[PDB]
Amino acid sequence: NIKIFSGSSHQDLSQKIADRLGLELGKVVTKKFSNQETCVEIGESVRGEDVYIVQSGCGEINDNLMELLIMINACKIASASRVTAVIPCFPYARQDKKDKSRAPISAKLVANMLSVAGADHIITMDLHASPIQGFFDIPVDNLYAEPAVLKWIRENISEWRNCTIVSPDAGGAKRVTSIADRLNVDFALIHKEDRMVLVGDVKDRVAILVDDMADTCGTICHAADKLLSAGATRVYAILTHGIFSGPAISRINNACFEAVVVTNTIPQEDKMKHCSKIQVIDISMILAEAIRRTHNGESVSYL
Amino acid sequence: NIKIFSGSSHQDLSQKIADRLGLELGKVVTKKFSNQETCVEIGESVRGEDVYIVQSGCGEINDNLMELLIMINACKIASASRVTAVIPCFPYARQDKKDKSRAPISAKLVANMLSVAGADHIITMDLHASPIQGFFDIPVDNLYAEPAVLKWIRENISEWRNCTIVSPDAGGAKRVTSIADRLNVDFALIHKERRMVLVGDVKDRVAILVDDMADTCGTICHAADKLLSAGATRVYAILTHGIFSGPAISRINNACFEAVVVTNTIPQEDKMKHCSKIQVIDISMILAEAIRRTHNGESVSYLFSHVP
Amino acid sequence: NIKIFSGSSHQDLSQKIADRLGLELGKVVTKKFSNQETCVEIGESVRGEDVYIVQSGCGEINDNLMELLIMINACKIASASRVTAVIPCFPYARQDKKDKSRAPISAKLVANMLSVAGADHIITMDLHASPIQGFFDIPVDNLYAEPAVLKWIRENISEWRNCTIVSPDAGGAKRVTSIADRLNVDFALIHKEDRMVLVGDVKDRVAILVDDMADTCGTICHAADKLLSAGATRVYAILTHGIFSGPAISRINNACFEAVVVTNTIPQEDKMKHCSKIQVIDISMILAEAIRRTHNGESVSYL
Amino acid sequence: NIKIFSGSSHQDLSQKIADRLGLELGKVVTKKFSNQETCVEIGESVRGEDVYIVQSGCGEINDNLMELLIMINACKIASASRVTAVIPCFPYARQDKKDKSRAPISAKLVANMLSVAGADHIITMDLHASPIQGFFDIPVDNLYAEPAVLKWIRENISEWRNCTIVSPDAGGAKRVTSIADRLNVDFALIHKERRMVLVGDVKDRVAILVDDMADTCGTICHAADKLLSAGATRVYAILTHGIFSGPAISRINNACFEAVVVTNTIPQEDKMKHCSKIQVIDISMILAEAIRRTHNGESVSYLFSHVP
Amino acid sequence: NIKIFSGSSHQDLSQKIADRLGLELGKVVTKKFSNQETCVEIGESVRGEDVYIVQSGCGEINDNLMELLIMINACKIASASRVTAVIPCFPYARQDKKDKSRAPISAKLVANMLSVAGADHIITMDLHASPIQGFFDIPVDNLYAEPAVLKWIRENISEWRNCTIVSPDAGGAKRVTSIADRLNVDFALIHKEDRMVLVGDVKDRVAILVDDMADTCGTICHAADKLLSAGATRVYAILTHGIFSGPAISRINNACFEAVVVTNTIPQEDKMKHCSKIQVIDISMILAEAIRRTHNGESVSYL
Amino acid sequence: NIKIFSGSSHQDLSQKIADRLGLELGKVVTKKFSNQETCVEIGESVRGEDVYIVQSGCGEINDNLMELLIMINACKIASASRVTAVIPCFPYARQDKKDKSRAPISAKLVANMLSVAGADHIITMDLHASPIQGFFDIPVDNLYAEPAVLKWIRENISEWRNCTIVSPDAGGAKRVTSIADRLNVDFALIHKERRMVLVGDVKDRVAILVDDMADTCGTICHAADKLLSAGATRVYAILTHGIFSGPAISRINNACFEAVVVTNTIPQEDKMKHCSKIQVIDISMILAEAIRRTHNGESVSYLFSHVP
């Protein structure tokens, strides 16, 4: 009854999920015309089946979006019983408000686009902001990296019991306080004035920069510099969604971090090779467990 | 062309907005069925008219929301050209994410209800979480009370050049930082773990608590003690939406605030008889300016930093 | 597979339904913030389940509506397989037309609101007017009190075989003729001119005022006075939905009725104590039987 | 700005309405594919124009409805500003509730079909059941023929001050009572059990049967006998929509009516050649006034008691 | 679980389908009021059932459309689990574009109408043009007469291996080339200038006019005349959907055709009697097989 | 009232259209997040304005489509009166039917995406398959490049009175026949079986290949050889949309075309540096005329046979 397809050139998260549920990825012919046009063909019957599509991540976010949507549509009009988008890293997630601008709410657009394409259900992990669940009318099961992040800090940072979790921006206070509370450590927060400012006890104690995602690393790199000026013993970088394009990769190595943790929502294989301090948290079991429980009607709230 | 209406019998902000535009409020025949059903009649044509309905700060949120929905419908099926719901204090705004609970996202529900009732446009002020514009498909104008607040601090607080803007929770950091920056001053941040912890310098500085709303004032009072504990000279509380239900008035009067400042999105006339500390920023002109501009197609974003 | 929640402070109709199907009401935490805001939390997994919500009836119709809608939404975005609103007394049912006014069609609003909230199906009893089924695009199963009303008249009114069923208004002719036809008795009808008018043989015969609902009782009380002036032996009052607020309760006792029948669509417990002539028809078996048959795909048309 | 069109070839009411507004009917190229498919062409731009399409009383309801739907679509995808379907006699109106049967609510279906075809507005007259405005989300103007009827009774019936307004069924009580009250006279009510039973005094009074429509006239003729049986001096029948299909003309001519009065929502030109009793109230001005007002944004509710 | 209703006076295709699946057509009371108004009543419970409606074809296309839609709606609001429209001959299919006119896209209207009425799925055969699948948001399973047409040409036309398949219009090139390719024969095409023009080798070889549908036959009759002037040995006429109204019937007999093949998407029984050269391809097994496989979640792509 | 915007940085057709209407392009602040996310800002009010957004021929179709969608949304939630997406070359148009495959109908998907993003209207040119207007519910204006093509043939080809209009495939017959008829000349038809087969006379005639687009030019080059094989004097290729990706420029330069003619729906400035054969029909005036007319409510269908 259950069927899993991968949505890209990228099949390393998708294949990991299918193995854990004892399945083979669905047979799909995906091609790109010389004029950049995406061609997708479901090479099997998905009729009456419970279909799951895991998004790709070749670095290009529009191509990945379009193939995601094309696949959901291809499956819907082929009488799939239910289509879920399994999108650990929600595209355009930053654009969830106008921000004192004539700016799009692109997160709401993408939700409208996922809905109109045919999606009946969304599985995602650690949304930038949580109200993006409210952009959909369909059920959204948003998973948390929180348990997986906490487990790493406890098992890798030795001097954690008296460390400090730090937000790289103003709009990250909620997330770092929560991480701090569970570990009974202190928290701090950075705000770029541009001169950077720090608020919270960081002197002679392990500092861990936890954030949802870093693109150019420009913010998180200067965040490490500041923390070291403020006298933190050592510094870390936890980034659930690791986009890491352009100057980021090199910026991290010239940076002082003892370790830079990520989750394989975006494949670090080619970049782990160009940076040794990086470590990946496997989020496939969490995604596989959330697919089985969704298909069986079992509680995902435990996860 | 323009036509303003009010909800229930709490017609003060509506009248204030109506006054500033040189208009009368439109006639509504509205009593409640002893059954608790609301009956509305629109006592005049709205055919091809640019209608504005102002949500009433009476005090029963489900009654108010229902009446606002009923009036939006009445005008839409009476062939109004456009119905704009002017909702200074957006109901159920605090319920905008499931929050690792199995809860409804009530903000989205109210957004869907407003939409199907026939609403074409939204005018609102300082959404608890701004991302609520994303809960609609029709355009939303989210007005900032920030400018009006900054103007109040500059003239009512002498030590404003050296004060500290404080967030009572961790979800108000993006709000306190931007205010501190426009005044070019320090910011602080209180986080209640469940004890309050403060991060940022407030020693020998006036501290100004900034929030979107105050409801039982439990948090804002324990934050006043905390700030004065940490070396704050004096504590101000500034709220956009002042609900002050339950023990809040008892919370405010015994609290060590110099002053508690609220806009008149929720009426404060009675609450100032029982509480001297409460001062009111008049927002009616910002709302009036927003309606005028929406009608003439002129820039509403001009209000986002500039008090009319 | 089947799950039943109650929608209010009111759990006397809801618990009766759950007992009859051998169930416990679902665990739900409902709270009202000091600023009258409703907070609802489904304290269990409703995923893959066939969910039924029975509306509350603490006298307040907006609060009951909002919690009804909040619960349907809470269940829908928590991947409930199907949500039904079990609303014996359809809110705002009177407002099903403009009536030569710039008035809302609030019954259509409420239907739009129930739909947009997530409802897939509606169970209701004796709608004010029947076209309210046509306000929805989802299936509506409207049950009839008619069999339960007829059974009472036969088993309680001794001199029924030659009685007269009377409509308190002009727009009730259809309902009273039907009740009269099934019992092979005569019918009559009242119309307020305000001076009241009567049409139909009522002299020296049992009179039974049958209506869908009475709020202030103002109409139905003066209807009893008129019938007694026109010389009816004794007078009754059948009101499926008993709202009975404000002056109504006292108006009924100073009224001449031998009995005032209702159905427990709205709880009379506290008011039966303040009026002895009242009798309640239990509509729980009809609602419970209509839930089981809806869940099993069995015919409800028999009911 | 205004642009009126007609359906099929039954272009009399359309022309009458067009005449009263000083307009020509818009060019439509419309023949039927021998296959029974309808082909419509709009022989002119409607771009940014306020379009009105009048449903034709030709006589084949599914053909008429389809053509009305096709024309609404053509205008909408030709960038009309607004398309209003003017449907004097609303099709499938008698199917508005399931009725303890497993039947479709056809009224709602026609309402959904009109809506998705692209209709922005509805102008109609005396809906069999009024609650059909509730079957739409777009605004509906339900016109009353009542005023025109009352004016007809006052001048054509001398005994009107002492007559009795009769409902032929039990679903027409809310219609006969309101008419009786405006004339300040008695009302009666016939109920066919399945025999007719009459309640209310009609002795030595002119009796006036009032209905929304007449179709085979079975009911209205057995009601005429019944009334004269009960002591009625003479019987009139007044209908808003006069369909008169099947044996109705044979029913009318042998029936003891003094006169059978119908509006021209359904054409009566041929039916008066074969039946002398039939008199026509012209409704074209009420419809013309309704279109004019809808265009200028003036009060249409003025027509609800006042004949233009 | 499966239920089949016929949508008209016409029950010869519908009954053939039900027999092949071992079923009886659903009990339905359909009536037409003296004012041409359609009355339909589902004389049984369709609750929780997988419902299929096969359209009628009494020659009238609006009456058939309205009863089709009325039945889909009647079933949807009676809690049918799934409603499919089985419409071998898609109504208004010609009107799929404006054609340099202010013309309706009536095919899109009808799709909107089928959707809004309640349909969840469409089964159809050899659409005029294929993008009509794209007019729906629901799944559309469009079947092909191609295999059934090819089988007839091979088994009835003796000299086929060197014949020529001819399009009666310009917008039929795609269809005839495909038929020609599968049989390894040549193709030709006619275009009315009105003087007719021919392009493609037709001399002294069997000619077969293949088209989707002919109404007045005006085009296809003159197409036969031209082909005979151009010197084709014998001429045929393959028309999947045989509408054949007005002058068509007589035009075919005065025409020179050796045979005129059709499919019983539109009943030829009364007209086969008025023309002997006509032969019908039975499309009931294809429709019955497509219903069973849709209901069981099996592949229809094989068909 | 009118306001034109462009996509990405390919602002040539937008400027050309803007020039012909005596307007500047509206300010857009648009860089791409190194993450490949597009960020758009509308650097001016669009409140109550008739907005037009021109899809950019930059070359990355999913980026272009996304940016077009993002800009449509930005304008809609900034209370524009109307947003019209001007899409000369409609993306994913070749995917309009499943084609006995289990494929998406991408045309409909793009149509749904444009619709929910907030589009009120579509202006496009020569849809690969025209039936794409049927994929929308909002009005679509499908412009013909046909007139501009016919004008090009009449003046650039001397032998046009005796030429042959050729379809490179079998899906272009309804396009080549109508063109041949307006010039009153012969038509031909190439069908690649998978070898090309030609039907129709081309002996000692100039042959003109007519298509909706050219992409790798595989087909159009093998059709040129085929035509010259069959006795064609010389071969022209005329395309509305000239994409020329992959080996097309190598395909064109070695091919026996006299000339390859394209409209400027997709920019050709660079492609003419590398290929002399390529000539450009300017379509900007047809698009400018179409926008002007859409704004003033004047007939756009006038463009369907007549070059402005």
Image: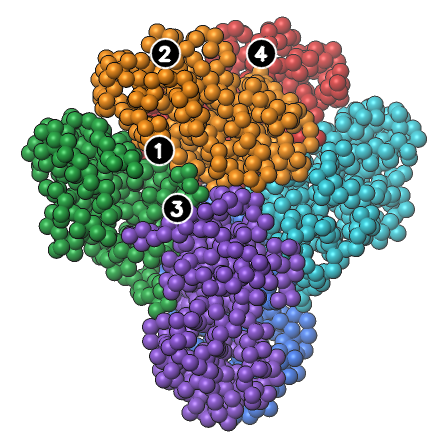
Chain colours: A cyan, B red, C orange, D green, E purple, F blue
Please tell me which residue lies in front, B143 or B241: B241
**Could you tell me how far apart the alpha carbons at marks 3 and 2 are, in whole angstroms?**
43 Å
Above or below for D159 versus B189: below
Classify residue C157 as left or right of residue A95. left
Q: Could one spot residue C151 in this view of the protein? A: yes
- Residue F157, image x and y in percent? 48, 84
Q: Secondary structure at mark 4?
A: loop
Q: Please name the residue that numbered disc 3 is placed on.
A: D106
Residue type marked 2: Glu
Q: Please name the residue that numbered disc 1 is placed on.
A: C97
* Between marks 1 and 2 in the image, the one whose residue lies nearer the viewer: 2
Q: Which chain does tag 3 point to?
A: D
**Could you tell me how far apart the alpha carbons at marks 4 and 2 are, in whole angstroms?**
46 Å
Quarter of the image holding residue E98? Answer: bottom left
Identify the residue at image location x=48%, y=67%. E265
Classify residue C133 as left or right of residue F65. left
Residue type marked 3: Ser
Q: Residues within 10 Å of mark 2 (few under 14, many from 20)?
A: some
* Disc ID at residue A229: none
Q: Which chain does tag 4 point to?
A: B
Q: Please name the residue that numbered disc 4 is placed on.
A: B246
In the rendered image, residues at marks 4 and 2 fall on the same chain: no
* Between marks 4 and 2 in the image, the one whose residue lies nearer the viewer: 2
Residue type marked 1: Lys
Q: Secondary structure at mark 3?
A: helix
Q: Please name the residue that numbered disc 2 is placed on.
A: C258
Identify the residue at image location x=55%, y=81%. E153
